[PDB]
Length: 111
RNA sequence: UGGGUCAAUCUUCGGAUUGGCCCUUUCU
Image 1: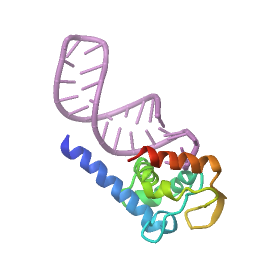
Image 2 (image 1 turned 60 degrees about the vertical axis):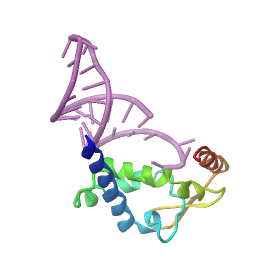
Image 3 (image 1 turned 60 degrees about the horizontal axis):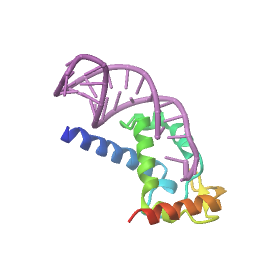
């Protein structure tokens, strides 16, 4: 049971690393972190076949975006009227006042 | 966030827990 939980963490690394390698404008946090389009998960799962070719499952792509968006740095960039971007960095929407408040609320809760 | 399914351990045998995969959920 000790190792069965480690393989899930590594399977989630591989999942998030695959996202950062194929869609860097959104998930390569070395360059920058920016708000993601609402419904980006649907756009990502349209590439589920290309990700399966390297071992990354649909459920693990979901588990990776969850990890990516619960980081404090992601919640910290959810500021009112910051641009949400698609998988290629293109502007598609803006962050609403409610969404910006809920984020700063989650940040305060943590820590 | 909920649901299905397979595998492992356990059970006071009513069940419970961990993990894989699929569907699904305002801030993805």
